[PDB]
Length: 103
Length: 103
Length: 103
Image 1: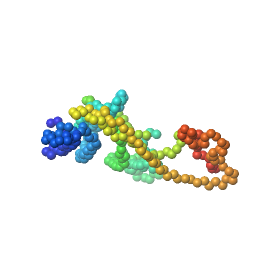
Image 2: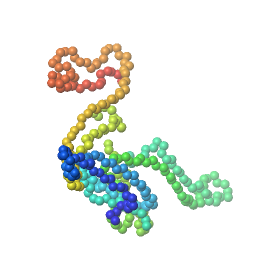
Image 3: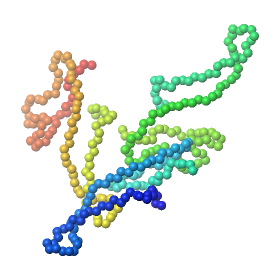
């Protein structure tokens, strides 16, 4: 109901966790679990590559169609572009329904 | 200079003419040429089939581009469409330069 | 117009960038982008190997030609050489037009 593709078997959850590296244990045995760990974080790169099937249009429509366009009118910032502080912003929600089809 | 394709050998001229069908000549010989012809015209259909080579675009441009679109704002007549009298009209000249390319 | 070789397809741009390595994120989730990165730079070596085609001269000229030469007159510094501070300098612009050819 939020829009999208209903999948009985969706793309699976990809779960990630730093392995606990303990600090130095006591030189005598303690049966209690470790509460002291070396503080650490991880970083790295992640790649997703999705292949999408397209459905081309076969309209015999004469007049031109509504399409998503940028405006040529000047502005302080180009849409879908970083500003002078390096902050990327998206100005408006772009839906996907621009071409037409007869019922 | 009016725009278009300069061709040393352009598509050739296709010339068409009704053959003169004379009216009844005099029953005696006259060496003068015929000035009296049966009034007639011709009609028919004409087909031109041109194949055009395209040049697809390879821009790595991030932001959206200016494109030719119809406006969705309502009007008494749809653009590039006959009116109530059956008269087809073209409202504006459409040029061909809408995509961009770097120098 | 600044001189040189006009190329429709020139040698391509070679673009280089340090990958951002973040500092430690907050232990709670924040949907804001990272503004804190580990300060780092890179260094290394770069090699360019260009092959040049030459065009040898076939003059039947009798007298000797103007050529680019160094002067033998003594000076505090040799031309196109570091000074006592290790600073390399080029004393004059050397053009390439020294041999002659008839029109």
